[PDB]
Image (cartoon, rainbow, N blue to C red; front, side, top):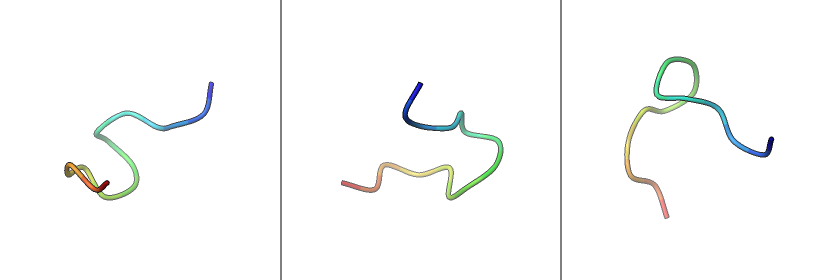
Amino acid sequence: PMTLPENYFSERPYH
């Protein structure tokens, strides 16, 4: 919808 799940890009709390 607007973001990917913790399984593709950086799976971290990036603000």
